Amino acid sequence: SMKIDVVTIFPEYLQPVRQSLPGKAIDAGLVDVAVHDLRRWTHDVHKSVDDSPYGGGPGMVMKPTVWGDALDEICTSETLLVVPTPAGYPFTQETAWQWSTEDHLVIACGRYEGIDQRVADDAATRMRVREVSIGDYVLNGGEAAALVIIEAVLRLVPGVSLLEGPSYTRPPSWRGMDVPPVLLSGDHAKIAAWRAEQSRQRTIERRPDLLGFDS
Amino acid sequence: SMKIDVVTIFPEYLQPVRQSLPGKAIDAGLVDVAVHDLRRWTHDVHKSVDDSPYGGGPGMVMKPTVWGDALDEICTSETLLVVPTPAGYPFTQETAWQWSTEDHLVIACGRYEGIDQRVADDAATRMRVREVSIGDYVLNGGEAAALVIIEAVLRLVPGVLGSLLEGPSYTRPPSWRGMDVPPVLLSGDHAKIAAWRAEQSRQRTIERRPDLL
Ligand SMILES: Nc1nc2cc(Br)ccc2s1
Image 1 (cartoon, helix red, strand yellow):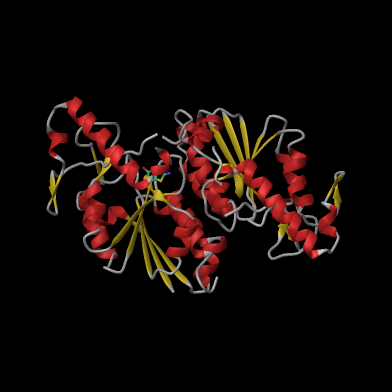
Image 2 (cartoon, rainbow over the protein chains, first blue to last red):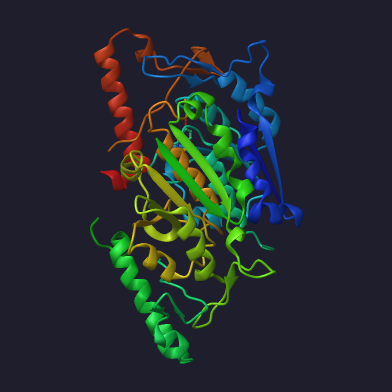
């Protein structure tokens, strides 16, 4: 049984956890996902969570005070605090396997130009903290990255390289395009070999890095 | 003017997109996002969208006849068909910039075991097709990847959503739980601040992303 808490100023954006794979995992009781509005930990009537950056720069930075109070309430020393950010360590399949065995993930979703660095620094004095990037692109906030991380982790929880090549299903001919004959041949060895080859050939074309080549 | 059509068996998943859109952008006709339930194009009373893989193996493959009908209705010659898949070319910020000037994106969300490859192959004979991965991990389906792609692309379209790594950021208060904001940031020496930020970026990139150097 895993607990996932997500902290965000847009709790509505996390509603997709209730569908597909995470929804099934929740219904099966293998995971509990709770979404928290960060503004719950504010005290002004304006419910401010952001302020201008020290040292200059565009945009706003999320205040450490509000985050600190939120994480104080939600986290324990056993928590794995996950902070999605384009500046993070890469989140990979290996990371997903690692986190699949955790009792408690707390995902802090930033907005504006990110979260005051002291939030992660302070949290790291009492729990494990992981700032991670899900890919080399910029979002407006961490919420979609939280959903990706939850999807990647939950499908690996007990109870739930190379690129996969093309797959096919019925009918054997469609619009004049035939399924590769070897796949219809029932020869397990030949099919295995063809699939292995297709995998390695797609990998060299689409992801040469995976095989130790440039680009 | 960008139109995005998303096709999925989980249309409710894509609701945050529509909710993410400022009314000003919609009323100005800058953007339109539509979500379509793939089962609209099923043929049978059981609304079947997948079937066992030829050549054997685990999982299911999505049916070409269903997807072919859906894309025939939704796509035109001007469409950029986007297919999220862990087996794709990498989706990066450069991709997002490229796609931000497209008139029509159609995002085909399938299970990771895949859509029958003839769907993309057929589509590619009359439109541009891009099979892409958003990272080096497997998701059960393309829906969360579609959310990431939509957000990364649309935030680059003026007014729609409202190298080295970035270093740390700070705001008030100047001291919090025993930690002070780096005094250089309060120095009023803006050339020095820029140099300090450059070094913080260098250190963070070496530590977290040595591949970038
Ligand atoms: N690719 C990603 N972009 C962002 C932007 C913000 Br603001 C917060 C988290 C993330 S993860």
